[PDB]
Length: 236
Image (cartoon, rainbow, N blue to C red; front, side):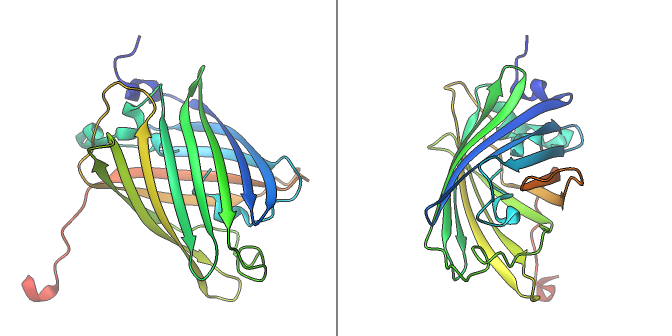
């Protein structure tokens, strides 16, 4: 018997992900599996495009395909909306605007099914350029560190989240992907509404040498942190 969602994350938790996508009319499905351990903010997953070739680069899907696995330090545990909403889950919705190119709109449900934390997602992408960095597969196979800023959404009883991913391109340029995100509880019970804070992300992208299908192996580390008030040196 558990009184708080965070109690479900004291050990290793199995994960499943299932994604149905449609980008410029190219339809695909992705299945993922692995495990998360919130005590050190780790996720490890393997994803497979089960319908054939992925029509977009794996790195553009990475933010879409589990913030409940962040490590929140003791002094911040009262700000962890994500686990508080468990086991019933939360909905996570985004629009991601790729600068000078198309956009993804996503809706996901993250919730326990039996002992397993399951992320089920629909993604629709429109207005992409056939010869742009996305459909043209010009992204490097990596995803650099990023800090995502979170604030409470009082009226929806959830949170709002914005961040700007800088995807590296083969030619040395970057491709910006503006993320706008909202999460709301699935259940009707109380959740923690957090003060403003950060999640620090790292992601390491690899391939399984024995895997011949289109796939991505992913490791994420995620830890929560507070903010500091920047000051211009003039004011110090």
